[PDB]
Image (cartoon, rainbow, N blue to C red; front, side, top):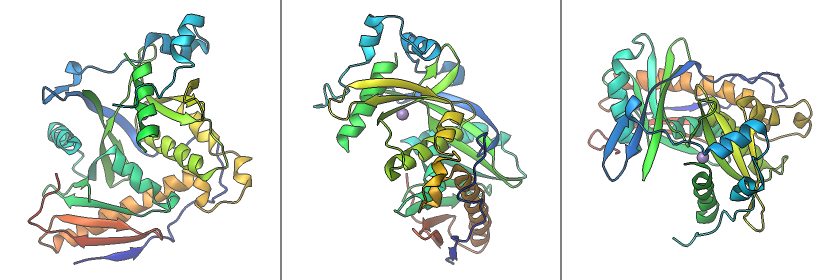
Amino acid sequence: GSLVLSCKKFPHVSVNYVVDKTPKLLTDCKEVHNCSYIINDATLLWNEASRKPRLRPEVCTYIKDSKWENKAVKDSFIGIDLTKGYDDNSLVILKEAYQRYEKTLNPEKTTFVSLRHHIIDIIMCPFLDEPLSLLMTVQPDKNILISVDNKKICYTGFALEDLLIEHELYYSIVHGSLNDEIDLLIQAEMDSINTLTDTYTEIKSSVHFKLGNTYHRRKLLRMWIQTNLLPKSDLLIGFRNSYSNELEQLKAYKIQDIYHKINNSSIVGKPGKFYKFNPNVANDWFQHIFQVLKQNLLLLSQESTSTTFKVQIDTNLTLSISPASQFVTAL
Ligand SMILES: [Mn+2]
């Protein structure tokens, strides 16, 4: 019926393992659909009908040249108080995306279907001091659906996207292979596209990184997982004055960049406690739980009345899989 399993002794490389070119989490990863969600209209505008959020041209210009067109331009961004004006369902889209691409799912593999948020959450377990909980339903088609069950730092983030981009949300549905027996159909919200480079660009707000500070090592590792799960994607980070909240610097990064930042022969000098936040360890952990999960959820299902399961993971990486009520749906 249920199941407990220790996953702390999962195969993985050395915490100190360094390698030059960042690894990849999914192979043959490609976007298979995309869509803008017009909220007031309760509409989904698929693919060629979707309105991609465009990164302002000045910014694209700045990213390319590595300098602003002129002082005026620069002052339209740098120095702006990302605080000014602070005093003021996703599972539905996924299910439509699954319905539109299903006939294209490889029938020889198990496909986990989920919003990017959850895949990231799972890869992070061993790097967090908090635990994990989620629902995983084994659909009649034998695939698996994953679902669920600081106002100011948050606002500066929307404020920054607003300042850099030209009510409505844009989703990218990608497909990638994990195993010889496992694929992922992931839904992810793109912040924007860099028009000059035809590359999604993930906007992040932050205070200058105090590396060697666990909080930032986490953020940087999560950032890496977040973009490295997509087929194409870059980052743009707005660094702000920890005091004024003024946007001090705009810095663009490729996945390689974020990777290097957290995988040096030098950085791995200080001893760690979370596998030193090593992207490769993360990658190994990735390969391990999903194999574990796919196997057991499949096994338990054949012997149960419930297609849905409560999946939990200890701070000790101990997996717990008990069946959920067959008379309840998580929307
Ligand atoms: Mn963002």
